[PDB]
Image (cartoon, helix red, strand yellow):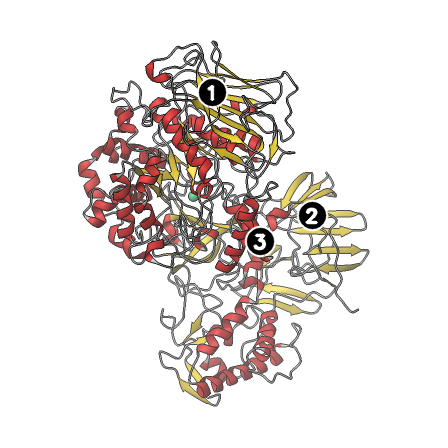
Amino acid sequence: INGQQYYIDPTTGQPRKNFLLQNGNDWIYFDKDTGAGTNALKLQFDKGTISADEQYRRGNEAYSYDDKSIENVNGYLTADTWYRPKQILKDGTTWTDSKETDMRPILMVWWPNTVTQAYYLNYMKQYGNLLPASLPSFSTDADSAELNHYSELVQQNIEKRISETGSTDWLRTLMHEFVTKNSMWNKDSENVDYGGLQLQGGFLKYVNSDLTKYANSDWRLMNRTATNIDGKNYGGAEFLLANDIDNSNPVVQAEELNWLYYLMNFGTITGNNPEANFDGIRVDAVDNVDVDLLSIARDYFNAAYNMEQSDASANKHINILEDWGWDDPAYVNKIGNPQLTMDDRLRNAIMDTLSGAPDKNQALNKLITQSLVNRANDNTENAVIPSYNFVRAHDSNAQDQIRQAIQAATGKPYGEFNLDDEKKGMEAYINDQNSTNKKWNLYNMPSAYTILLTNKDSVPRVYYGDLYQDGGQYMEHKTRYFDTITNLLKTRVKYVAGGQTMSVDKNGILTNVRFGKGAMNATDTGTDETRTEGIGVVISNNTNLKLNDGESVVLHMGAAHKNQKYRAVILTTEDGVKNYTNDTDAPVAYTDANGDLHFTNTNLDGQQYTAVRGYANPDVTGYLAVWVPAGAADDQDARTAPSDEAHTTKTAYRSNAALDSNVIYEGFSNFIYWPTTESERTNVRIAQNADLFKSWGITTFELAPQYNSSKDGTFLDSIIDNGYAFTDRYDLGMSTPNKYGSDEDLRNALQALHKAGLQAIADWVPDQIYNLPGKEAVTVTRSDDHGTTWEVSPIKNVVYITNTIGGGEYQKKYGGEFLDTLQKEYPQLFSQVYPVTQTTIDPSVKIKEWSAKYFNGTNILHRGAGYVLRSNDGKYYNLGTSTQQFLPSQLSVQDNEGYGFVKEGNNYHYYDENKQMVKDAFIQDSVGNWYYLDKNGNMVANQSPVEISSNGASGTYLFLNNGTSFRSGLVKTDAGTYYYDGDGRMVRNQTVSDGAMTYVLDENGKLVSESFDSSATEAHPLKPGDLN
Ligand SMILES: [Ca+2]
């Protein structure tokens, strides 16, 4: 009984918020907070008179407008501002001239309106006991004489408590707790939304303004990715996470080169050790930065390593791209393949045919065609775009599914967890991994890895979490796939080479063949070394596969393999798979004179598990078998060395037998735990295991990003501290260990890898920086991940407090410091003109500390739309440093009386700063609502649509009973339902999205249909193909 009322939306099953229901002259407004219905709106525009008591009035004035007198950010005041008054009412009794240290909250003496003053009183009473807790609530409607009486009493009681406790800490805490309970001062006014790449619930893009000139930029060219160089197209999302670096600013670009050089010379610079440098880069978040960076990195590598000279030259520095967009490969190829594109068409073919559940996988035929490379008869070299490929990665079918397991095991929201939670989720995740029916883990990991590692024209990348359990100390526990995948890896070195043929038969069974080194076509007879090389693969994704009697699967081993003995590498069993790491006790099969192997529904020569049929177990759902020639020498190596012959084209990597001889190891998971001893340190264990990785044929070890985590908990990366979320770009376990160890552990890992003949990859992360400690006022607009204005947000060209100043001691020590050396050693880098900026990089300014001018924007910070304090008509308070000096009445000697919104008779008027009545104009109140004063200067409030032209612009508006322009919501009337946009104007004849909601309005503005996208409402796994 006695509950609230709501209007349940038919598509959300939840209350409509900010929704007006009208029936004749009667109405219910359903509120913003919970959608609870009311028919009594409060007047929001009322200030009410300053202290009539002159001792309070004069005593509470600001001592001065100096920086030290009034807490501020670039001269702007915030809800948290404390200030020095002329006098304090000491111990509640004795007006006393203030000391410099006598700071008091501005909210002790000032409120944006009477609504907030009443709420302040209620709060200070209930939670501060600064009024008798017995008092009834102050209604918004309370007159200013009553409100002022009780805020003066609160002031007395604050001063008594300051005297009795000898402290103001309690008051700092209490006032900030009040602040955060006001929607104008919290996330409720920030239009939280998780659509697209709003991973943290929304962005604020930085814009130029006379209000914040020190934060202006001539650059901020956004979304300028591979398919949007000129900005005339859509491009990738500029915005992703945290503070988005403006990589279109030429000074920032020089700094990215500076950092790049630092990474590539890390051991030299920090350890006097040229044996402890990185050899290549991974470019993080490619489709979220100015694509100029690909050419800047290219140019540096060309200058320092002469990449384009030959294959031997390029292959000494394997670089890779995190480039998700399906049109990226053509562009990467065009600029010279300076970093390897991924082949996302190929990975998605694997996802679609092998990695899903039995009732979900598609026909295997797609593996032949859906890729940068057609593999039906891949018999040529240097003919395709070179690329790398993978089955999983730290952020690909790992982090989202692991968070799903944690959520399932703990009941906590997606992404929220402590270390105990993480371990409990990991136990469930690993139990799932070892099940036949998997909820969170990919199926057919053995078959997926077989395709990965036997494909021609591909640099495969192995994922750490497929060899070792994702969560645990580094390499603490092996997965069930460790033996299978390391068997494939060693077999790949020894046998996998030459041409490829892939086919799928009428039973949907896939056959994959490699001929061995020296043979490219099925008809080639090969060389001496070809004979005991090559591989044959049989794959099905059909758990019910049954061949009729007399039906066979034929592997066409080719003309180099006539009348030859083969032995098994992997066979599928009832319970899993069997691995054979060499010829000993492996089952055998013989080719005929055409080079064909013949398998059927029956074991060959009484050898267990040589029949082809469907299985369903935790390894295989379908069928897998792999065969190689018997009798290879123990030291057989089918790989090809890169030629040092001069390139005839302007390319680094070429897709050929030498590039194919490389394997990348992504040597981390996000869910590595912090080590409990020095011995458990990831980089310590990497150094100790260099020869192990070599034995798998790893040629480049991709290390995690080594940057010390911000540990701010604002994204997964700064919860599990993987190194992608950092404040100091140059701090690689240097001020304190990273999760992987100290900078000495890192240099030791690089040196040990080099000693074993492996390369090491530096994760280059130019997109963003986290957790800068210095505040800066910036003019911003709430925007989507492409910087498109969020139409329903009031945050449009609004001053907001950002955290953009800082960068740590190592950015300060090293930022810009290698530019002079780079200019003298590689001068050509400084005269290149880049395609997006159409200019050179700009090394004339060193970045030693970041500030807002260098960023495109920020994730929303939950400070609230109105945190920066304003009066009526959009006017900002300011000390006078960033914009016109203007202080609240209570702090100045100016009297508020008769200015702003004023009642006369049954009407309200608005008087401007010259005390003149405003007519036929829109005017904003201090908390951001909008009003229209008509031709007579009367506030409009008739809740029936009204046509207004304001500066040659039509609009149909609706003004609620309290005068406020209704906006960003629906109105249901007797005649239909209507939608008013973020500017208060009725929408007609279109489809509009309002956050999670989509509404279709006909020519008359009537709602025809609506839909709900729940994923806009909270953090969520990113949908497959979201980023293609
Ligand atoms: Ca960006």
Mark 2: few/some/many CA within 10 Å (<14, 14-19, 20+)? many
The kind of residue tagged 1 is Val
- Circle 3: element type: helix
Badge number at residue 800 = none
Which is in the foreground here, disc 1 or disc 3? 1
Q: Which residue is mark 1?
A: 513
- Alpha carbon of mark 1 to alpha carbon of mark 3: how far? 43 Å
The x and y percentages for residue 28 are 75, 60
Position of 300 relative to 1012 (above/below): above
Residue at screen point 41% across, 40% down: 289
Badge number at residue 407 = 3
Mark 1: few/some/many CA within 10 Å (<14, 14-19, 20+)? many
Disc 1, ligand 1: is the CB inside 8 Å? no
**Quadrant assignment, res 775:** bottom left
Position of 928 relative to 106 (above/below): above
Position of 43 relative to 590 (above/below): below
**Quadrant assignment, res 767:** top left
